[PDB]
Amino acid sequence: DIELTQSPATLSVTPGNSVSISCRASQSIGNRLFWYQQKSHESPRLLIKYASQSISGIPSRFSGSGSGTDFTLSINSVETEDLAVYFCQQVSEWPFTFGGGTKLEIK
Amino acid sequence: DIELTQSPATLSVTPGNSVSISCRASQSIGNRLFWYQQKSHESPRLLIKYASQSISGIPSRFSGSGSGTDFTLSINSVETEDLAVYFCQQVSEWPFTFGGGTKLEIK
Image (cartoon, rainbow over all chains, first blue to last red; front, side, top):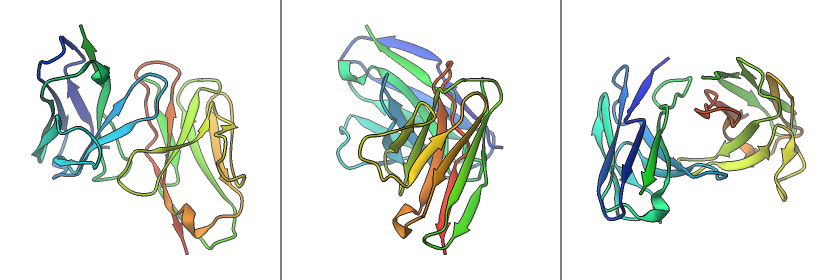
């Protein structure tokens, strides 16, 4: 089962800052990593597909990069509405497995 | 973490047949289990909340049951439009873990 380690666990910034969230796979999964946001009492929302492709309708401030085993999510200039947990997901090999999550707090 | 195991990985049916998808928690989580459907690389659609409460307006052929460790999503009379990957997520204790997914294939 491919394992996904996210970092950090939590982080705090004020609005306007940039943040990067990392996710590493225990083996090469190529570009087959998706990133999701989930705010409390909400279903997950897909931000990025295939490591670096953004979804129609999500802000240009989200982007991703990476391939093989190291992947990062960037939010350039976070907004207060970005307060959420973010997790990665591999779709390379079943069972499809998820990172443990990163809490973004916007102080 | 509370681990969720989903079964099967994929299954195949012909339209009109009935289908059962399972998701097992390693520890008791009562009714605290959400089911999702994803028809493509997109944000998940929430089908069932709290094990067995169907979301207003989803087809009546969908239902969920279970409380504790053993959860079942049932589609009673599949339509070809139901081709998707289904996931369960527990929402009982952090981190809110996900099953490995099940791909419904329609002969």
